Image (tube, rainbow, N blue to C red; front, side):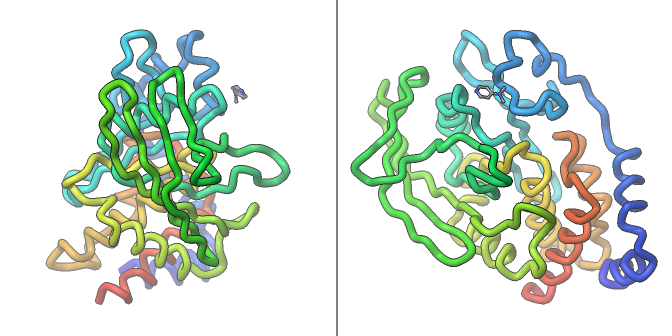
Length: 281
Ligand SMILES: CN(C)c1ccncc1
């Protein structure tokens, strides 16, 4: 059981050590398309690249590249698209990916400004009456409603394909209170937020995979997917204590590099799963 293993690593202060074992054990696959010089401007960080095997393609014949990975968890029957925070020049690409993959939800785990720098372009409208047109991808985006709570905001958006005049409702789940440094003290607000995304039906097999992002799409984004998958595996298995969080993280790293950036994020993920398991048992 991981609750016991938590006290072990904690009392022995071994988090840096576990985390390094995971670093060394993690898959390494080619990322050739990401490093093409034509794609340099489409990447927020030169050291964070999708693997060729798991990358999302845009359907535009011109240049199909976006910094986005499909994570398929076969036993949990859960998929996720992890992506970087959009750049000023890739906001149209982001929404074209959301349109093509038939996603129902976008989960955002960062503020647009953190530590006095832009972590992300402002890629959605701030006012009902000021909609956004992405000329490069022929899409229109409208704010329908916005529900601001203490720890997170939920927004209702209409995405319209100007080419075919089809429209879809997108839910934007924005966690607003992840601290600039370190991790939340308690995982309660994060778990609440994750249960709210689940309730929406954004994580359901009826729809395309949820799109999850922070700045790089590996740290906070990793914690989100890891917690959701582990909790779902605990519902599904005859013995819930058979779920090894290190095994699940390693399976997820076959699909995108660097998921969980720090030993703090690893500790927080254990804590989120352990606490979440109480609300599930
Ligand atoms: C490469 N990169 C992070 C950027 C591209 C375009 N505008 C601002 C930043």
